[PDB]
Amino acid sequence: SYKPVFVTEITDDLHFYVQDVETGTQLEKLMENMRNDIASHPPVEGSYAPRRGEFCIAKFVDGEWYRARVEKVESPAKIHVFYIDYGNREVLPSTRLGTLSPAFSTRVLPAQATEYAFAFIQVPQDDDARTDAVDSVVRDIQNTQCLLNVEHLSAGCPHVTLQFADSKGDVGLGLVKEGLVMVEVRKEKQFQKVITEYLNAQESAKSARLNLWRYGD
Amino acid sequence: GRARARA
């Protein structure tokens, strides 16, 4: 069952964050109400005190306040935050931090960004190859609605397949077809048909001498 | 505004 998601951020190690489209209006409503509350209780007159693991509000580069979590306090001028509804990280001064009121907590609405990786593909170990794959994904899916299916859990993030909204083409499989990534095989019998399809695309990418396979194998 | 889901 492929669910609609909005892809927000692509990491340098080929992970990505998504928002669930089904809860997008709930997030927007929370953000409108939180920002109305911030306007009546300006952080400048509030004296929040940032600490690691503590939630906060953080003012992003669009001049709007968002929900965040403090990850590291380097100095008063350098507080490292993670925007819990988007997945991006930022270093900011204390002038751009405030209290997250309980009315807008993750108990009221869960963190809206979830981190995933692509199922059935290996992240390239070579830096330039990895950059090529990340750049392809950023161009094709960053800040777009896609369809997502969770395939398997791992010792890290869950691994998923993504489809383009329009064509319904499998995004990860596209990378394999382009020779941008290698296939990661698994043993589960329910993945055998899809892994078979990915390996077939990989062999065709090798024959076409694309990207990873430009000079042969 | 900021790119985000349009539910």
Image: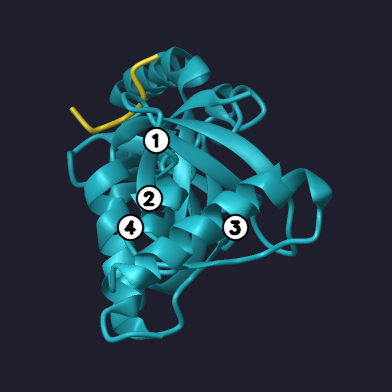
Q: Earlier in the sequence, mark 3 or mark 2?
A: 3
Q: In this orientation, which residue lies closer to the viewer: A203 or A138? A: A203
Chain identifier of the cyan chain = A
Q: Residue at x 36, y 49 (%)?
A: A9
Q: Are marks 4 and 3 in contact (CB under 8 Å)?
A: no
Q: Which residue is mark 3?
A: A120
Q: Residue at x 29, y 50 (%)?
A: A96
Give left or right: position of A215 versus A203: left
Q: Are marks 1 and 2 in contact (CB under 8 Å)?
A: yes
Q: State the mark number for residue A169.
A: 1
Q: State the mark number for residue A94.
A: 4
In which quadrant is the N terminus of chain A drawn? top right
Label 4, label 3: how many angstroms apart (C-alpha)? 42 Å
Label 3, label 2: how many angstroms apart (C-alpha)? 12 Å
Query: What chain does badge 4 belong to?
Result: A
Q: Earlier in the sequence, mark 4 or mark 3?
A: 4
Residue A76 visible in image: no
Label 3, label 1: how many angstroms apart (C-alpha)? 15 Å
Residue A194 visible in image: yes
Chain identifier of the yellow chain = B
Query: What chain does badge 3 belong to?
Result: A
Graded by Cα atoms within 10 Å as few (under 14), some (14 to 19) or many (20 or more), the crowding at tag 3 reads many
Q: In this orientation, which residue lies closer to the viewer: A110 or A178? A: A178
Residue A52, image x and y in percent?
57, 63
Amino acid type at image mark 2? Gly
Amino acid type at image mark 3? Phe
Q: Earlier in the sequence, mark 3 or mark 1?
A: 3
Q: Which of labels 4 and 3 is toward the front?
A: 3
Amino acid type at image mark 1? Gly
Label 4, label 1: how many angstroms apart (C-alpha)? 44 Å
Number of disc labels: 4
